[PDB]
Amino acid sequence: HPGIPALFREPPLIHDLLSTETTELQSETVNKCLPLLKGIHNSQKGPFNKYGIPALQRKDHLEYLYDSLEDYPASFVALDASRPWMVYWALAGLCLLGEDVTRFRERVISTFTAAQNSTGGIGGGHGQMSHVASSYAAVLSIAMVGGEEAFKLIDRKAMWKWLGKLKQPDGGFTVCEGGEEDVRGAYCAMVVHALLDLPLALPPEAEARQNGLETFTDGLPEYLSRCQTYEGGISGSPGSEAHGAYAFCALACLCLLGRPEVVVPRYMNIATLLPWLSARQYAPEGGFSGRTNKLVDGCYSHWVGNCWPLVQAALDGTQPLSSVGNLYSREGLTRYILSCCQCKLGGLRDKPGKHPDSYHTCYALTGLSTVQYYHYCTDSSVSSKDDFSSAFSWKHDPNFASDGQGSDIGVFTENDRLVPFHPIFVIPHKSAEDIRVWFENQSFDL
Amino acid sequence: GKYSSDPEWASIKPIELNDGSDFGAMPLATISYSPEYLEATSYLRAVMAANEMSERALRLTGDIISMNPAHYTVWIYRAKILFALGKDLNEEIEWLNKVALKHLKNYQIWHHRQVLMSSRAHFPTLPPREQDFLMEMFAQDAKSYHVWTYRHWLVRHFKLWDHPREIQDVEALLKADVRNNSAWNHRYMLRFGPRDENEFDAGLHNTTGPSSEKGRLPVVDEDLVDSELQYSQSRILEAPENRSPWSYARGVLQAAGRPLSEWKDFARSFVAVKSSHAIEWLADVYAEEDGSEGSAAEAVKMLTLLKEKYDPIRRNYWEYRIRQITASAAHATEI
Ligand SMILES: Cn1cncc1[C@@](N)(c1ccc(Cl)cc1)c1ccc2c(c1)c(-c1cccc(Cl)c1)cc(=O)n2C
Ligand SMILES: CC(C)=CCC/C(C)=C/CC/C(C)=C/COP(=O)(O)OP(=O)(O)O
Ligand SMILES: [K+]
Ligand SMILES: [Zn+2]
């Protein structure tokens, strides 16, 4: 197809003589991707657009996502502690593809009622201790289905008390009592905190108060700053290796603390963060890797991809009711997702040679959606308060499908257009707005 | 059932699964558990509800772990029992090693290891074969994020920054694969990571200062800096397109408060281009550290080579840099 640039049809120009495991894996990945990028693999379905890219197989992915909400055989026992995640990934994927998930309200309520602990928070299921990731997943799922009845399911005060137990003296959060402390924990905790409009102050008997801390955000951006590495990226805990997944968690968390152009440059060195984030993207694959010298992966279309609207807002500043534009290749990412990450029977995958799963389906679609919109923060918030005010001022305009060549073009078709997602909350803007506004108008339980 | 017929377990009644498959609508994403897993977890709910700290409960956690090592709750409960009963943690570590070897990609096992190992009463000093076991893991997956994370904690906990096996193991891994960025990251921590025990852990020095100065060392060992830079050049010469040693070198220079122009001639030797990292290095030298006329134009030339030939997927970033340099040069011409 003449609409496919040489950049996506050939290996890189520079090649070292030395062969190691790293280059062996990288070479194999490029070789698997090439026939798909070229659109000549027999597993691919059309129609192919003027850029030589297959359509998003909406019907196939819809069927996959609906099936993923039903029953699994005993072999899936490894997912037992992650059942709330499975609900979220499917609902998110369905929302992205334009489905009304209102009809799942009752089933969502039934699922999470059993998983909520009386001492507060939500765990992986009945008898499992509360965990920030399962609470995050449950809250976002509840946000998507909406309704007063789903909102009322959560014990707000208990959630607040439990989350208070996770606050650590160094400013971060553990994922559960006795569990690991990483920036994933901080991000999940603060999203739950923001969407439910929990009190900013720590519970009066929180252990962290013995360490001089008074609020959930005390010491937090400092903790996140200590997770930046010499590479410019952000690691899971201080001293660990920079990784796209933790870069998203850290940046999203910072943007929950204030305006991106204030908080991000203050706590992160953007001069090192920017090139490291840029370096996540490979050619000819087009997709993002998670860390230096490892492989592209469709889920980083979200983790790395959604770092970009946050960083770009930090550079542009708040828009009142001039931009640096997109600093990555939207064409490349779109080619990787649509040409390489679609499974013929439905669902999306990490990379060619991998089976699809609902996690990779959710995040590849989330990344595809982000390239289709201009996401920016404004001076107009749907929040009636000032805490997380900037986080609820995010708005969106469509970035329409392009014609011809260019450095920043939309190579998806308009038939491929997905619903926009909030870059921090990873749900539709209206869903995040509705849940936050509802809780803001509820008095805190006694 | 196993537990339901064991006299060891007669004294306690299991708590049956409540998934909401009786009340209201049908739950989502259900799993048809094996009868063995159903029974074990029903007894686990019972012992956890009673806060039971016993040998039988300990065995139970081991059984459930053998069926599902990604059960986060059971690991935490297991740790509680081990400390409450004053169990031999050396034996627990030997058991944990076997679980780790069976489940390479499981990270819960490694938080558990940290919890146990952090106990000074049981592990006052670095166990004599702990570093060897880490190398047994790295021999199977040299970039395992969770094992590297554990090793960082281990170094800080036992103060192993200058321990010869830490640097030796890093160099063994870099010999096997010079592109192992996890090994380079650990090397930075050993050589330039903050060590002050009265401070919170950080990946970089000077996080209390301006973010642009993040990484700056309070006191600089100049001979160590020279040695690390020389090491970086030697590895680069083995494979110039390898990003890791170039990034490490930028980190060392930032920490030492030295300019990128210290490597100007080294970078030029790869330019007929044998390394795009050498091109990006020169771009920064000409743009940020060279105040002479024509230097701005040369930086733009370098960035143009990158956007058109040597790293074109990052065109929008290169162009952003070009715009920054153009504006800066215009401001310079203005004044
Ligand atoms: C590192 N990674 C990159 N892509 C997918 C993976 C992961 N190794 C992983 C591991 C831990 C975590 Cl917190 C996030 C991702 C992965 C790999 C396959 C996965 C799962 C996760 C998970 C999963 C499980 C629980 C938490 C999360 Cl965020 C993801 C689900 C699933 O069905 N499969 C096939
Ligand atoms: C909210 C949410 C839970 C945030 C976290 C999501 C993210 C994917 C977590 C994992 C990051 C890291 C440990 C990956 C390493 O595994 P790997 O070596 O298999 O992958 P890699 O080669 O791409 O680095
Ligand atoms: K998780
Ligand atoms: Zn992935």
Image: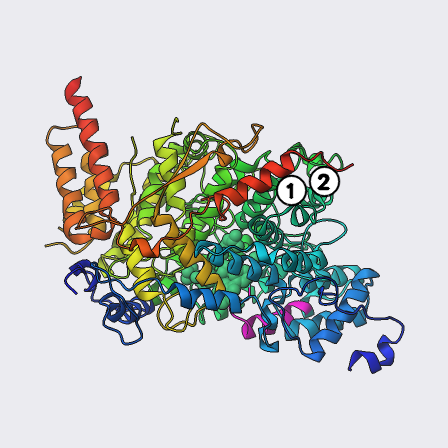
Q: Is residue B127 left or right of residue A391?
A: right
**Residue at 30% from the left image edge and 66% from the top image edge:** A26
- Could you say where residue B137 lies in the image, as x and y percent from the top left? 49, 69
Which residue position holds label 2? A207
- Could you say where residue B322 lies in the image, as x and y percent from the top left? 20, 37
Query: Which quadrant holds the N terminus of chain B?
Result: bottom right
On screen, residue A265 above or below A149: above
What amino acid type should be assigned to the residue bearing mark 1? Lys
- Residue A226 in view of the camera: no
Choose the circle earlier in sequence order: 1 or 2. Answer: 1
Q: Find out if the beta carbon at label 2 lies less than 8 Å from the nearest ligand 3 atom.
A: no
Q: Residues within 10 Å of mark 1 (few under 14, many from 20)?
A: many
**Circles 1 and 2: CB distance less than 8 Å?**
yes
In the rendered image, residues at marks 1 and 2 fall on the same chain: yes
- Could you say where residue B53 lies in the image, as x and y percent from the top left? 81, 63
Mark 1 chain? A
Residue segment shown in magenta: B92-106
What amino acid type should be assigned to the residue bearing mark 2? Glu
Question: Taken as a whole, is the magenta stretch helix, strand or loop?
Answer: helix
